[PDB]
Image (cartoon, rainbow, N blue to C red; front, side):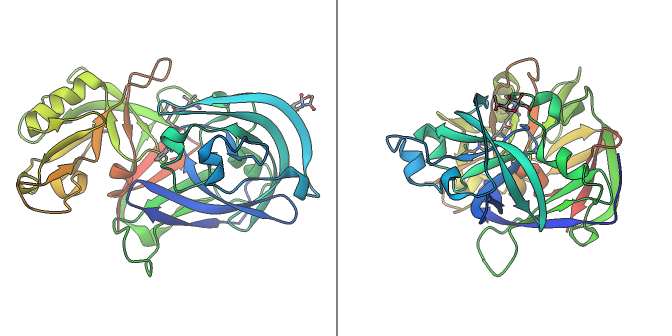
Length: 340
Ligand SMILES: CC(C)[C@H](C[C@H](O)[C@@H](N)CN1CC(=O)N(c2ccccc2Cl)CC1(C)C)C(=O)NCC(C)(C)C(N)=O
Ligand SMILES: *[C@@H]1O[C@H](CO)[C@@H](O)[C@H](O)[C@H]1NC(C)=O
């Protein structure tokens, strides 16, 4: 592990507080893509030009055309990434990728199959896994791992900043610091919690409480920080409990409450690493109205991650929006500091 004296930031655009993506360049000349940086997975893919136009998701997204890159290097091994919400498939390809000014030779997947649901709802073109190599499908080396290998980053860590406001443009949707963290988006001190098992940004969850009582997971559970997840999530069971206390009316893909009821919803604290990270209703309730005739969805819902990783709580944007997060690959730890 060689540490340099560099840092690199990636400006992120905030889409409806559910999607945060930056741009990256691939091939020569560079072909730009909108990608979400996902600590949940570990691979890199962008929709490929060799993707049938019968997949409408490919018709609506930028497509990488290896035939246009002079730096491209063929591989072709079949690849499939099975996320808990959708799946993509294609083949491995190598080319130069430019991220935050940094340039690195990277092996990535060219997707030739992306189902309309959920990808037609994706404002980004692809993903950049920030997970560990151990979880990389096809044993493909994670982009960050390769970067670290250049011996230029200051620390074997990267931080995430997600802005609340999604509507303003003049402001920055978010920021990722490769090689450290940015003191301008957090205040106070960082409080760490080591990873449980290596190869996964997952940690011990000593309990989730909904306001008054500690009505959830008294025996403990795990929380996986997914900077590529729109919301916070618990096992279908746990959430039926958590919502019950909120009085949310469960629907097909989420829970809602009458808009008037929104403000008077109780806080929700996650006990992590010996600290209570509490959220107020305003932090997990898409207000958007105050009428009792209207419905307002919650930035929280059920999602059961299959084993070996699951079951587990997933802390996504809804959590990172309030708590600036540092990922420490050096000490298998995750720091949480109050965003600013
Ligand atoms: C384990 C789980 C937390 C993890 C979750 C996963 O990273 C997601 N955040 C990825 N995401 C799921 C999703 O629905 N995303 C999404 C968000 C809004 C609109 C459309 C989409 Cl497609 C974003 C992405 C980044 C595509 C997972 O399913 N990993 C796959 C696997 C387990 C195979 C792995 N590679 O480790
Ligand atoms: C793809 O890369 C892997 C890893 O180095 C290599 O073993 C494989 O042969 C490559 N694909 C081919 C056959 O070109």
